[PDB]
Amino acid sequence: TIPHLAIDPFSLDFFDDPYPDQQTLRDAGPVVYLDKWNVYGVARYAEVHAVLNDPTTFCSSRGVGLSDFKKEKPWRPPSLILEADPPAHTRPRAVLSKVLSPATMKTIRDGFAAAADAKVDELLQRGCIDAIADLAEAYPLSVFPDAMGLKQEGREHLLPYAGLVFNAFGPPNELRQTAIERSAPHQAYVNEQCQRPNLAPGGFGACIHAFTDTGEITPDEAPLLVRSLLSAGLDTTVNGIGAAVYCLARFPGELQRLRSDPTLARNAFEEAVRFESPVQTFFRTTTREVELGGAVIGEGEKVLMFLGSANRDPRRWSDPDLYDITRKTSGHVGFGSGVHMCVGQLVARLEGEVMLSALARKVAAIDIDGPVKRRFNNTLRGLESLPVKLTPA
Ligand code: HEM
Ligand SMILES: CNc1ccc(C(=O)O)cc1
Ligand SMILES: [Cl-]
């Protein structure tokens, strides 16, 4: 009843151009089996959405990568939020919701916006820049590590570490094995910085530690939650912003509309998140035999959710392969959905918004003017290099 496919969604050939394979995956059926990795797969919006919102059946505590924590040792101590199910999940999540709260963004918006503006003005002086290294990477590094309350020394370990985490959700392919075989320095740096003495008061980390007082988390839980932010909070935004600049680079009409109404800044980023889906895929593990899309999946089975595919499903979206900054993007799963839906989404959207706002106000044109290079990661989709010429407004 279930189609078996030999598509490797973690192959380089797939990353280079996933969309035809994603159509094949959608059109093959509501549930596919990927013989390559002995996992179930879901590529349509409906089923991906269904799986995300059924955490009691499709659990996270056996890992949200290919590896089953019930079968193998996790490569690092499990995340107390990402790789946990309710109820253990519930209370750490609340802490992160409050640390990264509506109230908190107020405290950082002026600086994040100022940092975005200064960067765009800086890049306009050079004229020809790499929209990755000089913008997508430089800007988040200039605000987010500080917002964490991180010291200056050692931050070069941050992106490599994030690169690793997202590779480690993947299968035991060369990317993962290669990523993990060189994690010691990154782990040591990040893990050391999660300790309270190393985190500046006022920053997200110290704020996380401050919450041990409420009974919501113990002191020994705080560093891993600090660790979560240092895992998820930087490289994602890099690829989201990079995605957004690339989209604006490829859809000049939409750049022009953005220029004509900078208050479209927040949704053009949101649309970019849908359109590129910086986080491409996650797994769940079935806790029981279960019917999904008329397909019966056994207990203890891995189910691969194609978030990017769900976000390009024509069953749900009109003209999905088109970037439209006034689209109603609500319901996209680029940030997930349900109890694990991105707890850092406000930081990401703030960063993206104020940068796209700066671009909208300061830049007249963005033209690709060099070889474009894709960055390969088992979970993250984004570019290694995007040479562009910025024309000032
Ligand atoms: C473009 C930017 C981002 C994208 C596309 C993204 C994507 C996602 C997705 C898909 C999930 C769901 C994971 C799952 O259901 O298994 C998630 C959760 C999470 N995100 Fe992000 N994220 C972004 C930015 C951020 C930021 C800025 C932070 C922190 C400052 C962050 C930290 C986290 C954490 C800790 C979780 C786990 C939440 C939970 O398990 O309840 N992410 N994100
Ligand atoms: C969805 N992206 C995430 C990656 C890692 C973590 C974590 O370290 O908990 C959380 C979210
Ligand atoms: Cl670690």
Image (cartoon, rainbow, N blue to C red):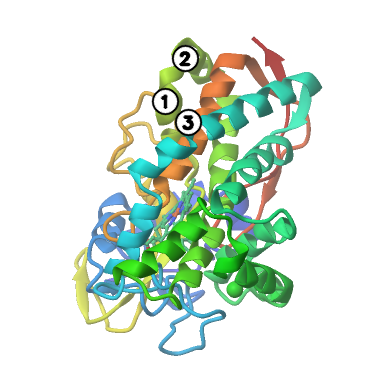
Residue 72 x, y percent position in the rendering? 49, 88
Residue 257 is tagged as: 2
Camera-side residue of 89 and 330: 89
Q: CA distance from mark 1 to mark 3?
A: 12 Å
Q: CA distance from mark 2 to mark 3?
A: 15 Å
Q: Position of residue 252 (x, y in %)?
A: 56, 18
Say which of marks 1 and 3 sits in front: 3
Residue that label 1 marks: 325
Name the amino acid type tagged 1.
Ile
**Is label 2 in contact with label 3 (beta carbons under 8 Å)?**
no
Give the amino acid at mark 2: Arg
Question: Which of 365/393 is in front?
Answer: 393
Residue at 41% x, 46% y is 345
Is label 2 in a helix, a strand or a loop?
helix
Q: Is residue 334 above or below residue 130?
A: below
| Label 1 with label 2: CB-CB less than 8 Å | yes
- Name above or below for residue 343 compared with residue 81: above
Between residue 293 and residue 329, name the one nearer to us: 329
Mark pair 1, 2: CA separation: 8 Å
- In the structure shown, which secondary structural element does the residue marked by tag 1 occupy? loop
Q: Residue at x 54, y 34 (%)?
A: 112
The mark closer to the camera, 2 or 3, is: 3
